[PDB]
Image: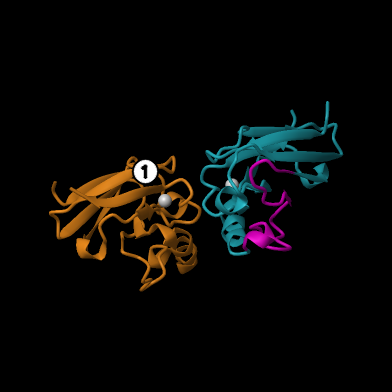
Chain colours: A orange, B cyan
Amino acid sequence: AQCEATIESNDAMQYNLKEMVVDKSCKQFTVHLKHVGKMAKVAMGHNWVLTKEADKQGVATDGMNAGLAQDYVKAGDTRVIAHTKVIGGGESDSVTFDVSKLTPGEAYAYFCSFPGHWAMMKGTLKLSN
Amino acid sequence: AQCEATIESNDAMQYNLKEMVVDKSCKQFTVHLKHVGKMAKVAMGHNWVLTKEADKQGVATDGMNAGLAQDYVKAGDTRVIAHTKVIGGGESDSVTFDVSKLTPGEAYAYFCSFPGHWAMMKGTLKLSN
Ligand SMILES: [Cu+2]
Ligand SMILES: [Cu+2]
């Protein structure tokens, strides 16, 4: 139902959710990302980035090149639907986005853009009723 | 006996050895790194890099900026005692170095300098006793 979801990231380099569903009644959707580990952001920071599935690699690449001060996301990347900041163990961050950016029936990829994390930290997001 | 060791790396971002000992009877030592997972190097490439414990973070930071083609290790890095190339699943690489670069009693760190892997893929190397 409600237009929110909580996802956990840890020191093992995993998310705890592999799929997220945004209910069709939602106009706004909020993702709460938590880092439940204890490692520093420079060593094991995590974020949550949303792109079309297609755009995964590219956004990941450019993000890595953007640096930590940019939360490992190329500024103004248009391929990026929404993203959180990079957070370390014990922290959390939230992002709220307009559902209208998503198109029904389409596949969206969410992943962590911190260097090298995208390969193990990825999931699918979809709009459904 | 031998002045050689095999160390495995996998898709879970781990090495299978946490510590390595080089026998004092050795003049040279060879490390054979194997990537026994099935991920490709662009997503989960691994290397093996040896430095003094203290040069870890810096070598890693800078190897990261050298890129894949440079095996994620800055060329001519004086802090690097030895390193293999970056390999992907189903591949192996070997590196041999002089034992005399080592100092009896000292703990050296070995780790994977591929983006983001250092936090998890790290161990200790030293001389026999
Ligand atoms: Cu991450
Ligand atoms: Cu690695």
Residue drawn at x 28%, y 54% is A105
Question: Residue beneath label 1, please?
Answer: A15
Q: Is residue A47 visible?
A: no
Report if residue B81 lies within the magenta region.
yes
Question: Viewed as shown, does residue A118 lie left or right of B65?
Answer: left
Residue A118 lies, in percent from the top left, at 46, 52
Q: Is residue A39 above or below residue A50?
A: above
Question: Which corner quadrant of the image does residue B98 belong to?
Answer: top right
Q: Nearer the viewer, residue A123 or B63?
A: A123
Q: Is residue A3 above or below residue A101?
A: above
Question: Viewed as shown, does residue A13 lie left or right of A125?
Answer: right
Q: Which residues are magenta?
A: B67-92
Report if residue A129 lies within the magenta region.
no
Residue A18 lies, in percent from the top left, at 35, 43
* Secondary structure at numbered mark 1: loop
Q: The N terminus of chain B is located in which quarter?
A: top right
Q: Residue furthest bottom?
A: A76
- Judge the density around disc 1: few (<14), some (14-19), many (≥20) Cα neighbours within 10 Å: many
Question: Which corner quadrant of the image does residue A11 belong to?
Answer: top left
Residue B24 lies, in percent from the top left, at 81, 32
- Specify the principal SS of the magenta part: loop
Q: The C terminus of chain B is located in which quarter?
A: top right
Residue drawn at x 37%, y 47% is A123
Residue drawn at x 34%, y 54% is A107
Residue B54 lies, in percent from the top left, at 60, 50
The count of marks equals: 1
Q: Nearer the viewer, residue B17 or B79?
A: B17
